[PDB]
Image (cartoon, rainbow over all chains, first blue to last red; front, side, top):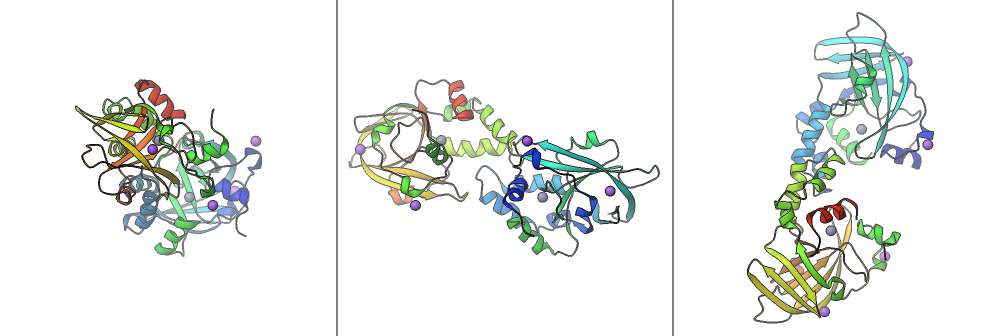
Length: 186
Length: 186
Ligand code: NA
Ligand code: NA
Ligand code: NA
Ligand code: NA
Ligand SMILES: [Zn+2]
Ligand SMILES: [Zn+2]
């Protein structure tokens, strides 16, 4: 099902807090690929060129740099199924069963808002991040099309303060051109 | 009289063409100062810092550079009264009686729109620019609060293509802090 007007506005960072709801980890079920490799190859260049073309105060160089810092990660693949998140970091792999920890509504310096969905790995000897936060422009149950994930081992509160790095994941099957297509429209 | 909702939207580059009307040169009557000197002194820095703070894809450096190219001019003062525009360019002065040449509605790369109000100096031995275009976020008769002015000697059509340089003028009496105040709010 395509987006209602309330969902479209919420995706653009405009929503009433009263509409925000809990979501289950299953919203992010599936196999996913980091888009960072496509920034590196130059394959996301059309996205940044359109962003630049549309705002004369911006430059390609600066927009790319912002997304470089945003996307950068060595976790190339993430798999989510049956309450478990699996992380593929170069040749290291880790997984853990995550417990839901609620959501947090944020207001950004821009005046736009977003909701993060918080999860915790409750192991001692897990190599997987203790704290994970999903942010995907959705404020109520809906299967994700792509997500940013904040990963940390210190606390949720501390992770909530991270604003510059947000490794970003699209469905594993997509090629670079389909990722670009979605970024330019969806 | 403060702005109606239609005027506020039009100032943000959103309007129906059916609402656009001719304006008389008297809308720009008064004495005016270039804001370029205030960019140079650093006194516009708070404006660019707010612009940067509000959009993480932008930088201060790039925003300032864009406005540097926009504001740059040696025409420090302009006076308008009785159908005549007077230009003070360092120690040179020129003036001419301008005839109204209509308006042109433009759509920018950003999808925002604006209206330019066209005037011509019809002399041979005038040192004043032959073609002048006012652009001030107003689409119908209203006394200007500040304006961009495109100045050229080649043709109106050619001047219509200028997008990067737009020397910008606020009422002559204002100090730097009042200019900043207006830029941050009005
Ligand atoms: Na509310
Ligand atoms: Na769970
Ligand atoms: Na119309
Ligand atoms: Na006139
Ligand atoms: Zn996104
Ligand atoms: Zn202006």
